Image: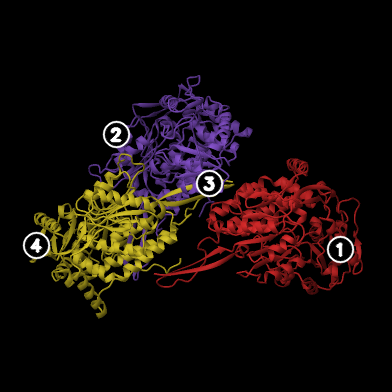
Chain colours: A purple, B yellow, C red
């Protein structure tokens, strides 16, 4: 190793005056630039288009936070040509050189931390700490993948020798692929999905989520200053499925890296399985498609600790997380004690403009607002509404922390991903039943258990079928390197982000023998 | 390690009297066993059916090597139920226990080596050494995967620690899957495709190729004797696409491991990408789909060494190998010298009943014979026939070693996998043109270069785009452990068999954190 | 590793206002609970008895600090049955699970640090820092052994392979044993002696020292909350030798872990060597039996540094340490300079109620007071009393720092462990003679040398025969992991605590071969 061992970027808590002052300055700088226009980034240069996209402030939707160019099929094709042209030489860069490029990008991002956080606050409605955790995670992905990539350097494969021959196996990148990023972690996941494949020699065309095109553009400003060769990374903000569909079904797209809804993920995986006219390979598609995550609490748990972790997991970033606790499974002995504590804590949560650092900002868009409110109506017909369930005053998309009790395990609100501040509480007889209910959903991303009984925790370690399980702590905020992130079942293909194994997905192996 | 380091099983050459005596007795006993009936193997027991399948001797098709039961949808469903029931407990076996079971199976297979080789001679027409290499490779897969599986034992993932927490990541098997094996390596690949997934905790339903159902049954006799728990491995010989289609599209099949034609592989990959009604996961499909492999020879090569390697690569097992040299690319200076030597060597090759240990036995079936002969007719209008090109006298499916020269790079016989004793010779100006022609096919499995020029060899190491490349030696016969086997492009998904990476394909990762 | 690398728990110095405030609050909480009664802990539950034991405050013996139940043979038998019942399943727990249980216990103990320290202050008379070091050491043992235990996980033995066979050697725990703990480190050593054996699969019956039964009970409150399965750890406070003798001589006690006086240690080792009626194994007995530790100072030393280290080593916790400097060996050139400095420092030491954080609290009991005063009388007949040697005013067992000079090397006070604040100074001609005198005792636990001469230090490294040797620093306070603790000769069996080797003592090995 030529750099210090990996360490996670500290998440700013803003408990110091300096931190608060720095954030206020960043917020002012960002809003003073709400009128900025960000073009597409293709072949190492910013390319503008006739049509544009408008990004709004979810805390005040009548306020524009920026505009960007709008990519169509023509621009997607141009980006693909640039990506393949770049791949021809980028794949030959020594891994040490590619890793240093990533490290430079991380250093540049770290120096623009407050700016990016403030952009997240205004563009997607994250409060201060949620914003800082997002940017810190992005930095972590860059730092982690830069180091992990070196573990695959030429020639990395362990093989059995043979007399009179040299047998050498090594990894090579796949080619040019497309990244389809989410709006809930538009800096962190957007960055990770791009730099992971790029680190080992692939080139990428990235389509940011419509609701977060501005912060995505700022991330590309960092890639540009870092010096990635033209074509290695491309930025294509767009409206609708045009760009994404064109690339996913393209015969010359080598791989697809996607994080988003199951609905879209299913279509992408199906399309990737088809041989487009003239295609000369089997496409690889990696998809992370959300979950319906539960936290189980039994009668032996520290009820106050459990309540706190549940509230953080259920309402952090307004519950707009694939890892969010949307189900609370309580055994009979823990039902009343835990529910009472959860309600008392939840009712004290503040909701308002994200920049004022409330416990909850607004949901991301009018469409998201419509979906969450629709699920709330569905919930009133399946469970018992005991807290919230209403839209709050203001143009911003403010929704109150909501809790439904007596929810049947197979109810729609207990099975479908709402992606909003809505928690469904389910009462069960014992721990065995808690596990059965926890596992009975089409998903398997995150899960948690609050209990002091060792046998219950170890039982869950072996039987709570989720990719990321947490005991006596929140189930959100997986840290790069510490907790490989990815799920089972309909939560995706188990592409563990923030783990050594992630990079292997973007490599193929060659074995070369020479008989002397 | 608790066993000796892995070593490849020696391939018998039958040069000693002892080896010849043992082989003659084995061949006689197998022949005297002609007509035997082998049932299906489901849930730890042999289960017969009303309908049956017949396996013929390609060297004398009027002879019935044996018959087997015929599985339908009902039997497939029963096998799937047994496989999932077995998975529940098999996945919990300590890895050391599962690995010892594999080692036992390898010891049992080793003691039945001559019998298995003799069965290959009669059922699929392999001469003696081709048969020995096949069985040796099967033993190698078992020995290799038994050891490789231990490298993934609980808790195998390297993670970054975090204060006040235990963070443990580990691998777990996927579930019950289906294996669709080829007829050309019915002991080796059949075995490898099954024991790899099983070694790490998965359960399998195996469908042998129609032309090799008898030897597949004998491999299952070994699995049964070894003691694999009921349901862990299941044997389902069948006719047509019924069984395979039913399982590949089944909502309860977790993964598909396939080796065969590109036509079938494309259909399987597409089907695996769809969510069958009620399916609760994204299916994994691994496919190895053949190739159009070339050997390049330039003017600096040892022409005699090259000619020998080309003949072995092109005509071994009648060219019925995904790794077979079906293209010979000669630079201008090497054209006449190498072609003259190849023709002289090829015309001396003996062809006849496999039991006689000829250089070439028969092709595997009447349909395969028809297809190869059809391609020969096509080739006559594309290139210049200079050797063979016809069926020989006899009931067996005997085809003479065939050579076409001055073949256009884009001719059908220079692009499509014939899978028969047909070599297409292409004349190019220089090495650069040779590499261009070598890469210009939809495949990328094996390739070779005969040259003394270091710069050409190293150039090919970087640019001859195939998964398994060989210099100054044959391009067939990849050894387990020594040469990870798998290709690029339409040759498949690059699932490298006989390599540590192979087992990772049949595992998913879980990350569990406990905050103390 | 799944947790951060081991680090020693910092020892609180109470130099901050917060630390002092926290201690004062803990002291108040502890004394407000002086009326508490603590039962025995058997089979996962607190079990009370008719008879009780009273624990007194050595700084004010008329004040009761708590009462506990009193175990007899019947309770010892009940605990033994519970321990064996638990062993049957506890031995099968994955090591990772057992280690996590220890880590939980450490976290719980860390959260109750001040409470435990305050209990040590009131129950055994430790001043503030001595109390904090004790609790910190206990936490260290738990953290260290939890990690060290994983180094022995299945299958940990390195063996030579053999053809056609699997040869696997692994460790397994012994069974149920008894722990007999000391009163001088009633949290640290009490904890270490228990959790070490327990971590690798053994079960334990622990008998706390009579003078420290209350703090021992509080440690068990931690074990109970942590969740050790019923029977794994048992608490049996008792009076006299009844409980200890019954268990040590029991045919069903597998091992004995003891730390205490040589008198008792000799009897335990002798008893362990006998086969009790019906016994089916050779008992293992580990004993740490004190010492008569010396610090040598030659004429090249930093006299001020030496004097400070000597005073700390001789009078820390009133000299009631197996590692305490009870002999000061001075070469002629260092005699006057060092003795003068030692006397000036020692005469400034404060003595009084432990809660006021004096340099010295009271000795632990009336019996200890009687013993120390008796040795002081013996000393007046062997050496020259130059400092202290008197009981101070107050009901508390306050004894002044004492120094005898011109002490013959073979005098009783220069050979027998006083375990009180009594230092014997011996003058010698040169370093060679210093080593001879240092080695001429029946013990060999700790020792120290203050010198700047490299040749003298390295000479001592090779010839000062003690298990724990220190150069130019105090000879007490061995840190877990840093300084494996244990001695030679009559100081014990050299069971190095806080070292990887410690756990091996509680394991036996099995070798299993399978011929395939």
In the rendered structure, the answer to whether residue C217 lies left or right of residue A247 reads right
Find the distance from the CA under tag 3 to the CA under tag 4.
Answer: 72 Å
First reached walking from the N terminus: tag 2 or tag 3 = 2
Residue holding disc 4: B390
Residue holding disc 1: C339
Which disc number belongs to residue A74? 2
Q: Dot 4: within a 10 Å radius of its alpha carbon, few (fewer than 14), some, or many (20 or more) residues? A: some
In the rendered structure, the answer to whether residue A8 lies left or right of residue A266 reads right
The chain under label 2 reads A
Find the distance from the CA under tag 2 to the CA under tag 3.
Answer: 56 Å
Q: Dot 3: within a 10 Å radius of its alpha carbon, few (fewer than 14), some, or many (20 or more) residues? A: some
Residue found at the far left of this picture: B393
Find the distance from the CA under tag 2 to the CA under tag 1.
Answer: 93 Å
Give the structural element (helix, strand or loop) at label 4.
Answer: loop
Q: Position of residue A301 (x, y in %)?
A: 58, 41
Give the structural element (helix, strand or loop) at label 2.
Answer: helix
Instruction: Report if residue B29 is visible in the image.
Output: yes
Find the distance from the CA under tag 1 to the CA under tag 4.
Answer: 111 Å
Residue found at the far bottom of this picture: B17
Q: Position of residue A57 (x, y in %)?
A: 47, 25
For the residues carrying marks 2 and 1, which lies nearer the camera in this image? 1
The chain under label 4 reads B
For the residues carrying marks 3 and 1, which lies nearer the camera in this image? 3
Rendered position, B84 above or below A316: below
């Amino acid at each position: 190793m030529t750099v210090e061992p990996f360490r996670n970027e500290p998440i700013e808590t803003f408990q110091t005056e300096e931190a608060r002052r720095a954030m206020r300055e960043a917020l002012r700088r960002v809003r003073e630039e709400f009128g900025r226009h960000y073009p597409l980034y293709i072949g190492g240069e910013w390319v503008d288009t006739k049509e544009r996209m408008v990004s709004l402030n979810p805390s005040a939707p009548s306020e524009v936070v920026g505009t960007t160019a709008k990519a169509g099929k023509a621009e997607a094709e141009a980006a693909l040509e640039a990506a393949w042209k770049a791949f021809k030489t980028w794949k030959d860069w020594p891994q040490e050189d590619r890793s240093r490029l990533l490290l430079k990008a991380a250093a540049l991002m770290r120096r623009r931390k407050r700016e990016l956080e403030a952009t997240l606050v205004y563009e997607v409605g994250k409060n201060w700490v949620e914003a800082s955790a997002d940017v810190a995670e992005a930095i972590d992905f860059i730092e982690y993948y830069a180091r992990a990539a070196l573990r695959y350097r030429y020639p990395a494969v362990e093989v059995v020798p043979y007399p009179g021959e040299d047998n050498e196996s090594f990894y090579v990148p796949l080619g040019a692929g497309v990244v389809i990023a989410p709006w809930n972690f538009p800096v962190a996941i957007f960055t990770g999905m791009i730099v992971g494949p790029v680190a080992v020699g692939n080139t990428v065309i990235a389509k940011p989520a419509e609701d977060a095109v501005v912060v995505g553009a700022k991330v590309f400003e960092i890639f540009h200053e870092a010096g990635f060769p033209p074509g290695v990374v491309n930025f294509l903000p767009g409206v609708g499925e045009e760009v994404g569909a064109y690339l996913v079904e393209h015969p010359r797209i080598r791989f697809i890296n996607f994080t988003g809804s199951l609905e879209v993920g299913l279509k992408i995986y199906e399309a990737a399985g088809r041989l487009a006219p003239g295609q000369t390979w089997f496409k690889r598609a990696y998809v992370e498609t959300g979950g319906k995550n539960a936290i189980i609490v039994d009668e032996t748990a520290d009820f106050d600790l459990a309540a706190e972790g549940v509230v953080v997991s259920a309402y952090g970033f307004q519950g707009q997380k694939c890892s969010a606790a949307s189900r609370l499974i309580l055994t009979q002995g823990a039902y009343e004690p835990v529910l009472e504590r959860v309600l008392k804590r939840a009712e004290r949560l503040s909701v308002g403009p994200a920049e004022e650092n409330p416990d909850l900002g607004p949901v991301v868009s009018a469409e998201q607002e419509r979906k969450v409110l629709s699920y709330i109506e569905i919930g009133k017909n399946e469970g018992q509404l005991v807290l919230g369930g209403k839209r709050l005053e203001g143009e911003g998309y403010f929704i109150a922390p909501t809790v439904f009790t007596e929810v049947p395990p197979k109810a729609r609100i207990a099975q479908e991903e709402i992606f909003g501040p809505v928690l469904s509480v389910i009462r069960v007889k014992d721990f065995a039943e808690a596990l059965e209910v926890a596992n009975d959903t089409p998903y398997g991303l995150t899960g948690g258990v609050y209990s002091r009984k060792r046998e219950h925790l170890e039982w869950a370690r072996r039987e709570f079928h989720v990719g990321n399980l947490y005991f006596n702590r929140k189930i959100t905020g997986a840290l790069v390197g510490v907790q490989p992130f990815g799920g089972f079942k309909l939560s995706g293909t188990n592409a563990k982000t923030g783990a050594l194994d992630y990079l292997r997905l973007f490599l193929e192996m060659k074995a070369v023998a020479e008989r002397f």
